[PDB]
Image (cartoon, grey):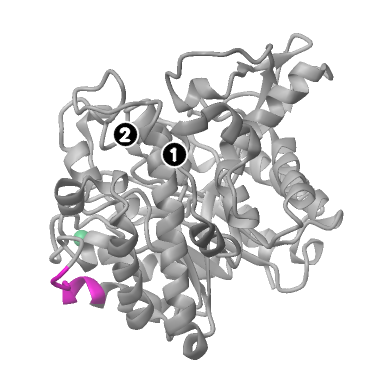
Amino acid sequence: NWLGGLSRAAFPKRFVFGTVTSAYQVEGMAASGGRGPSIWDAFAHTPGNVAGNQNGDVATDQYHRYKEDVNLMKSLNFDAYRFSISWSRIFPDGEGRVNQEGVAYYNNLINYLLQKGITPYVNLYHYDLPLALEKKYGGWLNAKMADLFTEYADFCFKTFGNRVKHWFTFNEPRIVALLGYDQGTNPPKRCTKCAAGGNSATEPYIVAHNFLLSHAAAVARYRTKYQAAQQGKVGIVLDFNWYEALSNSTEDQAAAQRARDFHIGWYLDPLINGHYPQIMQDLVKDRLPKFTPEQARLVKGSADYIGINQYTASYMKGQQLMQQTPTSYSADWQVTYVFAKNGKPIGPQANSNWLYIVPWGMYGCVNYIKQKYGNPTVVITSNGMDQPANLSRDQYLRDTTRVHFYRSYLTQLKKAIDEGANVAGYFAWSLLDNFEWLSGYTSKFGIVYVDFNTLERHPKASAYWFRDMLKH
Ligand SMILES: [Zn+2]
């Protein structure tokens, strides 16, 4: 049947299903309601940076329409909603003066969600550093971010935490490090070649270290000041795409494992075990910052659950490990990407070139975390695929590839859970077609279509699929 045997009964009791957005991608009102600019506002307003020179000034205008969108997600039988708070909408300069109008918006959103029986899962940060902090402090290159982020987090805990019980600090710090400071294609556009400056061999590691230290500091503040009264939880969201050895050779299996360690272990080994992966210590050496014993003890165990954003999988081919002049975080892995095996592609691509449709990658990732890291509580915090630009409304709505995508990926997640993986929830990226970063409005990830001329919402076939699967 079109559900393929899936329903709430096929998952654990009290398993959480939700949808996901982020502030800059859906809110709009980017320069209104008292919001200060983020590094993404500056980046997107520069000609050439985003597809079609588009930006998030208006986006889906969820700022004005949030009750429509909450009504819709309730009608589709979701239990929860993952969204982010824009740091610069609360603190336009990232520190100092509070924008009360911004505070009121998130109060209103949170209160309506609760009124409608949808649990808020709230991210503090989703790529959108206040531009003032980038300019004044140098953003995530500066260890002072720990203090700056903790003060912002403290405000959010105090202001919203009597109602919000499920927090995340960051979203995919690996992607910030990779695209912001290795390749230099996302803000602040730093890299060895880059006009803005940078060093692709050192800066990604500095940035990741500062995310880990800031996460740990924010959680320490939660636990020492707020947790007794509020009784909520705080985690982090990490991307993890699967790596499969191209062959059973020792060198191909070692390559796939190196890729896992440089991708997810970079954050998970510190968060679970209190140190960076051994292979990273061995290869990156003095370019990898060292936690002091005290810092390592603050980072270890500092995530109450691990959010995983899972989309795709790649084959990995190995090589003899060589002594090499450092060039970049990416080159440090000493692996070779491969997208076919035995003459067959690993899967077909969605609209995004990096997004190969590989449902068994979901099982791969979840099983791996279960087996390697002592089966921590995991929440799938994003999973989904995109349609291309320029389709007709009805073409967007008949999204049979996305229906197949969710049925297959959820069957694979179910397989892992039935084998004992401690997965507590699953969140579809995205509730709505939205501003997809460098792709702007040319990539459509939503289970709900948004007409970007009229701003009208129309649920796609995949939205009705969820509604059917999730009925109580
Ligand atoms: Zn509006």
> Which element is circle 1 on?
helix
Q: Would residue 156 be found to the left or right of residue 370 on screen?
A: left
Q: Would residue 45 be found to the left or right of residue 418 on screen?
A: left
Circle on res. 118: none
Which residue in the protein does label 1 denote? 175
Residue at (22% x, 54% y) in the render: 130
In the picture, the quarter occupied by the C terminus is bottom right
Q: Would residue 78 be found to the left or right of residue 175 on screen?
A: right
Give the quarter of the image for residue 276.
top right
Say above or below: 317 vs 139. Answer: above
> Which element is circle 2 on?
loop
* 101 part of magenta stretch: yes
Q: Considering only order in the chain, which callout, 1 or 2, is on the residue closer to the N terminus? A: 1
Say above or below: 433 vs 421. Answer: above
**Residue 348: % across, % down:** 63, 23
The amino acid on which the numbered mark 2 sits, given as a three-letter code, is: Asn
- In front: 387, or 216? 216
Residue lying furthest right: 419
Instruction: Tell me if I can see residue 353 in this picture.
Output: no
- In front: 438, or 349? 438
**Residue 418: % across, % down:** 85, 56
| Whether label 2 touches label 1, CB < 8 Å | yes
Residue stretch rendered in magenta on the structure: 96-103
The amino acid on which the numbered mark 1 sits, given as a three-letter code, is: Ile
Circle on res. 186: 2
Mark 1: few/some/many CA within 10 Å (<14, 14-19, 20+): some
Q: CA–CA distance between discs 2 and 1?
A: 9 Å
**Residue 454: % across, % down:** 26, 49
Say above or below: 132 vs 403. Answer: below
* 65 part of magenta stretch: no
**Residue 22: % across, % down:** 38, 55
